[PDB]
Image (tube, rainbow, N blue to C red):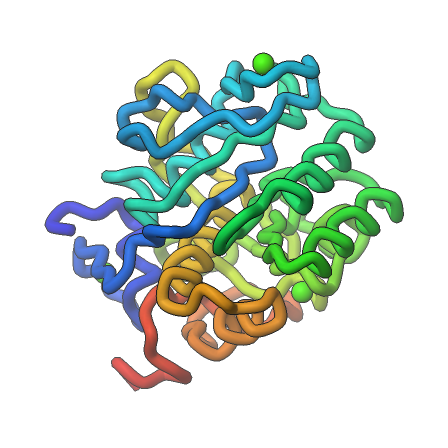
Length: 281
Ligand SMILES: [Ca+2]
Ligand SMILES: [Ca+2]
Ligand SMILES: [Ca+2]
């Protein structure tokens, strides 16, 4: 891409400086990203008819439309034509948070269970949300990954240990911290032994609920970046189990690139099939 926004620009290369290009060998055609969030604007122009409703566990209806913005934004980072990682992925909105972003643990669990029960082909869930400890929530996410669907999970935004947050602390999940375009850990991002890797989450431009656009920061913006490359990886290999996908995200990641990691493993999202440091050692 000749004029790529920074986050896409970053994940296709090993080192700074940025080159204003997002290169891709895949687009996640044939895979489906389940976005567990405030819903998603199916009619947004970034999706070109590739987003549909799943279910709405806040209002108990069939229309998972977004009235907050956040879930449209993360869905745009996964599969938006201009500002997305996997530009022909399928998006399925699963609405578990209200217009104000508030949700119950029961409703979020219902969305996780729904994804486990309804995923058909190559699939990946994205949970750009977090809060206090919850073994019941942890247990539902642990169960959906056991059924064969990889869950990307935001680390949290409190400059704290991600091990005290659910669902972030679930080991079998892929817990994602946030970075800026200078390769620093975003100053808000959670950290520690529960975080598997970093991805662009500071100042990310993506779709908004109103059909236009917005640029916001959070581990919620970081997470869909890696869900997006999960879909790239899944098109390349449809039969990747959660374990194999987690491994492939780990071994393809750029190493020792991030500053102020605070005891986090120093791995940065990399979207192409190269291993170690290869393309630029
Ligand atoms: Ca680039
Ligand atoms: Ca609805
Ligand atoms: Ca993990």
